[PDB]
Structures are given as structure tokens and as C-alpha cells.
View 1 (cartoon, helix red, strand yellow):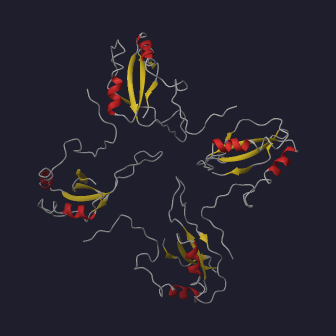
View 2: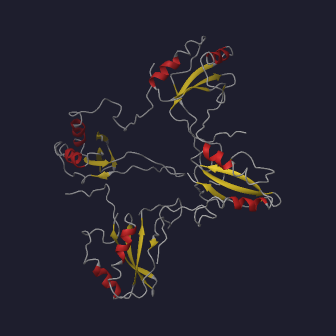
View 3: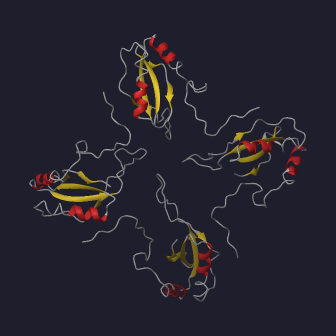
Length: 118
Length: 118
Length: 118
Length: 118
């Protein structure tokens, strides 16, 4: 038998139970997004913690992050999206970074995963 | 006359007012448990503190600890229970350890005492 | 003109606005108490801070301190009360000390002043 | 494009988005106040932070500061107002300083800006 470690083991949602992500594994999750006609975006924030309220159901703190520049309307290659992750990690090297994807027909997001840790 | 010291004197419930526990005194409290047909178990946790809530009677925080592997269904000797307290204190040497006992006819616990301090 | 200093200037109630208290000034406030037939006592506590509650009038925290040994029933000289302030300040040298006085006809206190600071 | 910095960038209200204020720019904002017949004043405080309350609209903490000596009733030159900012910054060199101006016909304030930072 074995015991799961309960001390200082935080998780970060989707694809967080697999071995660490490498290049040529991130470039394939963007090709699958572009051939379905979706729009990428970027985000960053220093601390990923959440809070609550005394007696209000459905309320939590810490769900909004800062948008890098603007959504990329009309991108067709996976190069301009891979060259913008380096400018962001050289100006704010002490924060987290996330990648999103939008859909306008149904008005909902489609992807979210982390690519950098402080 | 004499004065009880009120500064930095925490207590830990049952058998916490007697001189410190030694071996050949822990092995006798497990013999008395096995001849009444009860099931041992183990637990651990870093901090033993409790909290409250504004206006909810009968609610407190800090009453659940983590379970080591599983309850021992069918133990008959006090050696296998005394050899499992050493594996636990070499993997997590900075936590508390407690020993419990179970009854399945009345569905309640019967014993609880501490055997290690950080 | 002059300005009262608003930074780090705590006060401690009665007789706290006069020059610092000396001996041959504490012994005279006990003679006045004994000739009116009152009973002395002692107290101590580490921190003199108070708190409140959200919506409960007339409730505050931090009004109870610890009693030294027992009220002195039958004291008639100001020597046994002046020899008990030295045993207390040699066992707990990092706490405050207060002196009280009781009345058993109207069931109220009569005086309270501080004689030691950490 | 460019990105506004969201980390450690506090603001201080009016005239806080301009280049830093210099002399001969502070003396010209007091001449405009005196020729409209208003009364100057001074204030100081260590920390400019605000708080809230659970469910009370229109309530905030941290809006009152300490008054230096008294309002100047009858000032006619901008010298006595510029010589009182040096006595205040030599007695409390670790606090903020703010300048006000009153009106008695309509009973409201008219000006507010910072002139010193710790």
C-alpha cells in the first residue's frame, strides 16, 4: 500500500495530474484550436488563491486575471502565439500565465491551461 | 499555597495529567482493547487547533485527521500494531499521532490517546 | 501653541496623567483603604487589549485577569501587602500587576491602579 | 501597444496623474485660494488605507486625519502658510501631509492635495 501526501501539494486544474508539459506538446494544443476557428488570449496574476462570503451561495473571490494586450482577431499560424509568451515572461517574471480560447457562436470558453510558474 | 501556571500550558485530553507515558505502559492498553474484540487504527495531523462560527451552535473546526492506511480487520497480536508506529514517525516526523479503537455493535469509538509530539 | 502627540501614547486609567508613582506614595493609598475596612487583592495579565462584537451592545473582551492567591481576610497592617508584590514580580517578570479593593456591604470595588509595567 | 502596470502603483486623488509637483507650482495654488476668501488648514496621518463594513451602505474607514494647530482666520499673505509646512515635517518626518481650504457661505471644502510622502 501507499499513502497520498497531504502536505504542500497544490493542483492547478486541467492536465495537472500528468507529467510536466514540454515543447512540441504545447504547439499541438494550439493547432487543434485554430482548425476549429477559435480565438486565443493570454492572462497573468501573482497569486492563485480563493475566498468566500458568510452566507451568499455561488460567490467566490479570485476568478478574474489581467489581460495581456487584446484578443487576436484573425490569427492563422501558431508562430505569433508562440512568440508572445516570451515578451510576457521577460517583463513579469514573478507571476503565473494562462492561455484561453473563445467561441462566439455559443459565447463560452473552450480551453484553459498553465504554461509558467514563478 | 501554590499557583497554577496560566502561560503556555496546553493539554491533550485523556491521560494528559499523569506523568509522561513510557513503553510497557502503551503495550498494556492495546491488550485490554483486543480481548474486548475492537479494531485499532491510526491518525496524524500537523496542528491541533479549533475554531468556531458566529451563530451556529454545535459547530467547531479541527475535528478530522488523516487516516494512515486502513482499519486492521482481523488483528490478533500486539506486535503488528507496535511495528506500524515506526513507519509513520519516519515519513512524517513533524506531526502528531493518535491511536483509536472501534466498536461495530454500538457504532462508537472507545479509546483515544497520543503517542508522539513534534 | 503645542500639539498633543497621537503616536504610541497609551494610557492606563486612574492616576495615569500625573508624574510617575514612587514609594511612600503607594503606602499611603493602602492606609486610607484599611481604615475604611476594605479587603485588598492582586491580579496580573500579559496583554491589556480589548475587542468588540458585531452587533451586541455592552459586550467587550479583555476585562478579566488572574487572581494571585486569594483575598486577604483580616489584614490589619500595610506590611504583608507590601511584601507580596515582590514574590509576584520575581515569578512573572513579563506581565502587568494591579491592586484592587472590595466592599461587602454594597458589593462593589473601590480602587484600582497599576504598580508595575513589563 | 503598451500595458499599464498593475503591481504596486497606488494613486492619491487630485493632481496625482501629472509630473511631480515643484515649488513655484505650490505657491501659485495658494494665491488663487486667498483671492476667493477661503481659509487654509493642515493635516497629517501615518497610513492612508480604507476598510468597509459587512452590510452598511455608505460607510468607510480612514477618512479622518489629525489637525495641526487650528484654522488660520485672517491670513492675507502666502508666507505664513509656506513657513508652517517646515515645522510639521521636522517633528513628524514619517507621515503624510495634506492641505485643505474651507468655505463658510456654503459650508464645504474646496481644495485638497498632498505635499509630502514618507
